[PDB]
Length: 40
Length: 40
Image (cartoon, each protein chain N blue to C red):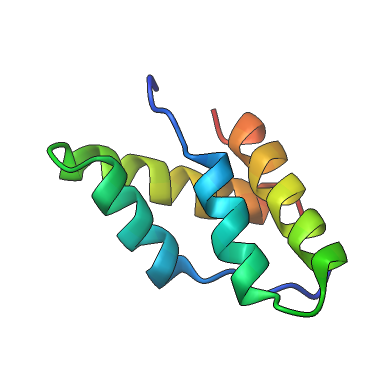
């Protein structure tokens, strides 16, 4: 699939969503990206 | 990992990001979710 995901904007969303757990922002973003690479 | 992702907010972000291709919003959200389930 030829689709581009705004990882910057998503990181900002998860950053806000995890307004305490930046470590969680990391884990969720890295799992989303990894998963994006797995679900290709 | 015990992490919750705002799929609603992300869908809105991708909806805005793909301000033309709602079909792409679908494909990206479904691949992010599937990938989330794969990268567990």
